[PDB]
């Protein structure tokens, strides 16, 4: 049993809810919250901007030190950093950004990072400002992640379309 409440069960291991990932993290304090990161860990907008704002910019300060030491992530890659006030850990995962022309096949590689964690609160990778089709992102998630993933979808309209269209 875990703390997550109000989710619809899609599969054995994948759950979904219409929720603000920031407000969900604040309530649950999950072991792992996933950030929709870019390779520079520049948390300007979308999910990353919202998570970072909720940490009062402490996520960005930590991230800048990580990049200064290690250099940029790979598209499809990840790093584990602090969850600050939101979670124990933040798994920063880089899905391909269609608005930069990145290979959508890298979305499966991105989701494979989730398998290193038994339970996660996450957004749909590569959707939102990254430009991918969220329906596709959900299919790749279900067909790739084997650990228990709780997906937060902010827009009620997209949430309802993801559920209604789910095979
Ligand atoms: O949650 C939403 O409504 C839209 C959304 C964002 Cl903002 C970021 C990543 C994935 C998705 Cl699906």
Image (tube, rainbow, N blue to C red):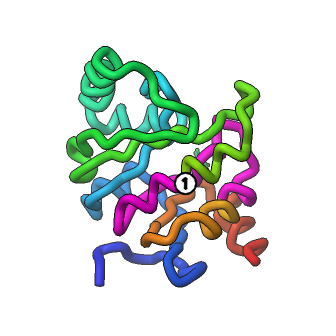
Q: Residues within 10 Å of mark 1 (few under 14, many from 20)?
A: many
Q: Position of residue 34 (x, y in %)?
A: 42, 50
Tell me where the magenta segment starts and ends, as one range: 111-137
Q: Position of residue 135 (x, y in %)?
A: 73, 59
Q: In the orientation shown, which residue stands out farthest toward the top?
A: 68
With respect to residue 17, does 84 lie above or below?
above
Which residue is located at x 59 percent, y 64 percent? 144
Label 1 residue SS? helix
| Residue 159 appears anywhere in the view | yes
Magenta segment: does it hold 120?
yes
Which residue is located at x 32 percent, y 56 percent? 32
Q: Nearer the viewer, residue 58 or 126?
A: 126
Q: Position of residue 15 (x, y in %)?
A: 51, 73
Magenta segment: does it hold 24?
no
Name which quarter of the figure residue 52 lies in. top left
Q: Position of residue 83 (x, y in %)?
A: 26, 45
With respect to residue 82, does 44 lie above or below?
above
């Amino acid at each position: 049993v875990n703390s997550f409440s109000g989710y619809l069960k899609l599969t054995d291991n994948v759950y979904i809810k219409n929720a603000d990932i920031v407000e969900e993290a604040k309530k649950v304090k999950p072991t792992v919250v996933v950030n929709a990161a870019n390779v520079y860990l520049k948390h300007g907008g979308g999910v990353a901007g919202a998570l970072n704002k909720a940490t009062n910019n402490a996520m960005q300060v930590e991230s800048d030190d990580y990049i200064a030491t290690n250099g940029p992530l790979k598209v499809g890659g990840s790093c584990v950093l602090s969850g600050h006030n939101l979670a124990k850990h933040c798994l920063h995962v880089v899905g391909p950004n269609v608005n930069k022309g990145e290979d959508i096949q890298l979305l499966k590689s991105a989701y494979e990072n989730f398998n290193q964690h038994e339970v996660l609160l996450a957004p749909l990778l590569s959707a939102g400002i990254f430009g991918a089709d969220p329906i596709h992102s959900l299919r790749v998630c279900v067909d790739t992640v084997r650990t228990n993933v709780y997906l937060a979808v902010f827009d009620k309209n997209l949430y309802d379309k993801l559920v209604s269209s789910f095979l």
